[PDB]
Image 1: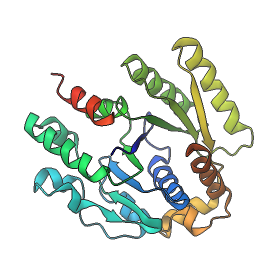
Image 2: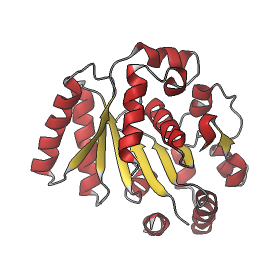
Image 3: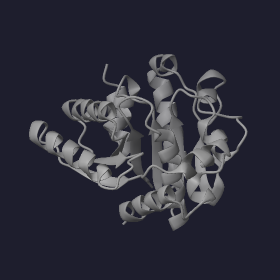
Length: 258
């Protein structure tokens, strides 16, 4: 059995992506779906910190101390499952053909028990990230209305597209401030991807500037949980609501193309 697979990504940092990943994941879980969030980024502790959970086991431990993957699944609120990160580029580069198979086989065994497998990707398309971005069923790219964030979102989509990713691109405009600013960015992005890449892109949703988000992060309770009525919380809940009604093959093939 295979879960639907989503890669959440951005062009460069400073866009609030990981926070958006966790909150979106929780929302989907709140609908009733079995969700597994994998932190594929370089930063140690994020999901756990965001959940008030103490750091312990992480994906990085599968590399260094050869722990099984299944051993690394943790429980979140709302029956969300996750695996924490802290894996570096040097870890992906050193992989054996035998070790990649071990990874994909362990991952497939774990993931078979979930409806959605969500990858919280590190920024950009470099190295192994490209393989994941070209294997998943959906790619969510997170951006802000800030004109430097938008330029990086375009470069990012052009990259993924030029590199042969056939997944649908959906945009999340975070920190809008709105109301129509959220739309103006999207529509602008949409015109230029359509014209120059001949790639059609969807708008997953707009998350308004909201004080609840900073309160949520500093007090380590995810915003949707903390304040389901906040403007940001309603927004993210709507994204999950609107979104919900052969991954390992492509991924294997791409990893072994050398």
